[PDB]
Image (cartoon, rainbow over all chains, first blue to last red; front, side):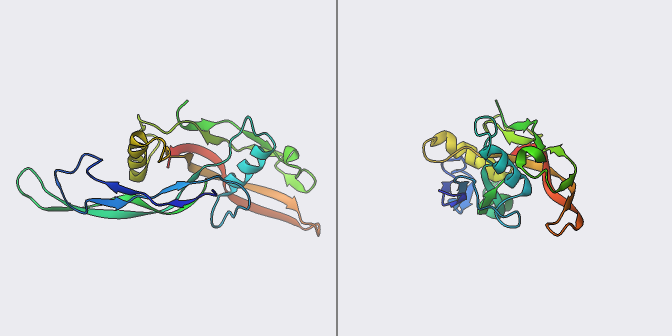
Length: 104
Length: 104
């Protein structure tokens, strides 16, 4: 249960685009989850602030929370879809897929 | 209650580092806390992935978590301190001061 990438497939049908969209029908979003605690590394899986915040949190747990597990690397996906007129449109959406997670 | 920056002063004395850290004595570190839900404000430049994750969380609160509230802008601080060898060292530390929080 440490801060890590969890798999998550998201279907455009559930997002309301089942009409326009030709392909893909969904994509692997994934998501970051898990607790942020030592060991931490300001050059890989954390920031300085996260480290300092963790320390401060350990010696004051009620008032200051742990940092939270969030993406460090996101990828784009491309979708092909229909228009009013039968226009086939290819469109790239950035920061759509989680590839890596870290404590922030 | 929403995702936002909170004041937090960090004194190197509370941390136990007063012995060797020459300057500064401490610094406004701040941190991020609070719910990531809609309305997902402009100022908090949420990624695409975050918009999706919030949606999916709404449909599956038990399965997928809310995005995590985390720094969008950090500042560096410089610290002057003694080595264990008594060398006087100056070192700019990045990602030290939380200046803005987003949803990630």
